[PDB]
């Protein structure tokens, strides 16, 4: 595998977004991953709609601003035959009625999705070398919340409570890291991103390797 991966450097990452006062990180994670594979497969970077998932992708498990799961995110887009753009179906940071007109408007599609084998950073690195990957981690602690620079090494629990997107990895000063795109806007972390420790084993740093998944497009 490559020593350094950064999907931003090849235009596969949309500018940092902000979920605001809404537990919709799951939708931002879904979208950033879908945005990335679309660029990789088609050559075009298009910003896509979180609100569509919040309004239209509710399940027994996935509940708009009350949290949810990226797998339901990917599933909705598969079942719907695609997703509308950010500009056409804009983010409001609150639960709205599903706009069926805008739901019929499809600019990006996916064929399938896959789960990364759990607790396997090597398999996670393998998937990240190919595309951005949706992950959940333990982001509730003081240190994670106040992170502004460097490689985050904890402390953090391992309970997945917040979804983000891995957009790369590297090493600096002998410390391996994942590059994480968060949805707390640009004033958090390293302009909205975090470098977080990689190759610690087990569930990964803050449980990052516990529930990794990514969308699939058959043709490049």
Image: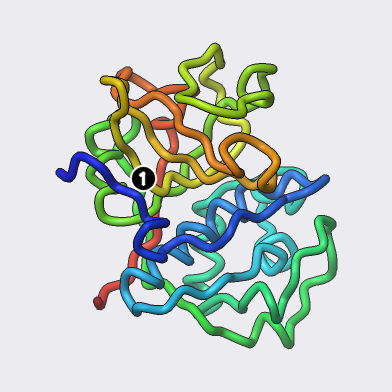
The crowding category of the residue bearing disc 1, from other C-alpha atoms within 10 Å (few below 14, some 14 to 19, many at least 20), is many
Task: Report x, y in % for residue 26.
Answer: 61, 48
Residue at 45% x, 24% y is 151
Nearest to the observer: residue 171 or residue 104: 171
Q: If the image is split into quadrants, where does the N terminus sit? A: top left
Residue at 49% x, 22% y is 152
Q: Residue furthest left?
A: 1
Nearest to the observer: residue 105 or residue 16: 16
Task: Report x, y in % for residue 74.
Answer: 49, 61
Nearest to the observer: residue 51 or residue 183: 183
Picture quarter containing residue 8? bottom left
Is residue 97 left or right of 137 when viewed as pictured?
Answer: right
How is the protein colored in the picture? rainbow
Q: Secondary structure at mark 1?
A: strand
Task: Report x, y in % for residue 97.
Answer: 84, 70
Residue at 53% x, 63% y is 14
Residue 2 higher or lower than 49, as above or below? above
Nearest to the observer: residue 99 or residue 190: 190
Q: How many numbered marks appear?
A: 1
Q: Residue furthest top?
A: 155
Q: If the image is split into quadrants, where does the C terminus sit? A: bottom left
Task: Report x, y in % for residue 109.
Answer: 46, 77
Residue at 70% x, 49% y is 24
* Residue at numbered disc 1: 168
Picture quarter containing residue 141? top right
Residue 127 higher or lower than 91, as above or below? above
Residue 41 higher or lower than 199, as above or below? below
């Amino acid at each position: 595998l490559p020593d350094y991966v950064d999907w931003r450097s090849s235009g596969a990452v949309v500018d940092i977004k902000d979920q605001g006062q809404c537990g919709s990180c799951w939708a931002f994670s879904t979208i950033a991953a879908v945005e990335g594979i679309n660029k990789i497969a088609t050559g075009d970077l298009i910003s896509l709609s979180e609100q569509e998932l919040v309004d239209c992708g509710r399940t027994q498990n996935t509940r708009g601003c009350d949290g949810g799961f990226m797998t339901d995110g990917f599933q909705f887009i598969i079942n719907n035959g695609g997703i509308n753009t950010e500009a056409n179906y804009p983010y409001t940071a609150e639960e709205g009625q599903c706009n069926l007109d805008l739901q019929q408007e499809k600019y990006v599609s996916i064929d399938t999705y896959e789960n990364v084998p759990y607790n396997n950073e090597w398999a996670l690195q393998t998937a990240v070398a190919y595309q951005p990957v949706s992950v959940a981690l333990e982001a509730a602690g003081y240190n994670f919340q106040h992170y502004s620079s460097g490689i985050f090494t904890g402390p953090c629990g391992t309970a997945v409570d917040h979804a983000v997107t891995i957009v790369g990895y590297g090493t600096e000063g002998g410390i391996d890291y994942w590059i994480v795109k968060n949805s707390w806007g640009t004033t958090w972390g390293e302009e909205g991103y975090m470098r977080i420790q990689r190759n610690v084993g087990g569930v990964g740093q803050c449980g990052i390797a516990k529930k990794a998944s990514y969308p699939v497009k058959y043709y490049n």
